[PDB]
Image (cartoon, rainbow, N blue to C red; front, side):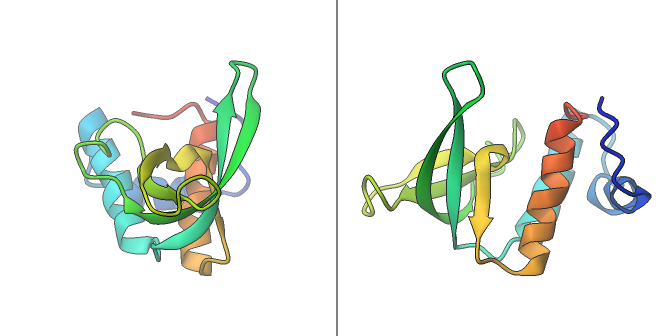
Length: 126
């Protein structure tokens, strides 16, 4: 996985709150989805730091997130519906939460995002 063990707090939260109810990949995705859906104070502004060019280039884009994607999407990865403030401001796309950096959100929203970024660095468990 990755040695990103910043402190055991997040390992504990993952195992005993985020995915405690899970068993297999679909249920682990639902565990993450339900925790984030309950925690994130969407709609909020964020930067979509789109991973690009197959070189980990970051094509940043400034967006307003509207909410998490449907559970049918959230079975496959964590995703959010977003409106491109710098390209539409009147239409909506979908982005990976893994490629989003929220702006001026609450601590609990930032916490869920940070917690997910450790799981991203880990190379996942679903």
